[PDB]
Image (cartoon, rainbow, N blue to C red; front, top):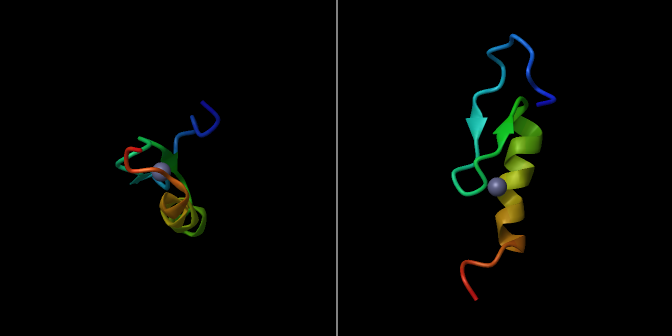
Length: 41
Ligand SMILES: [Zn+2]
């Protein structure tokens, strides 16, 4: 993985995507991108 560096800065997981983030700002953006998702449909 890209973020496979020895750093404890990456501790943000999106529960739906399983995505690991290292920064808060892009994380919240990704969590705001849930509005672009489809619950089921
Ligand atoms: Zn996500």
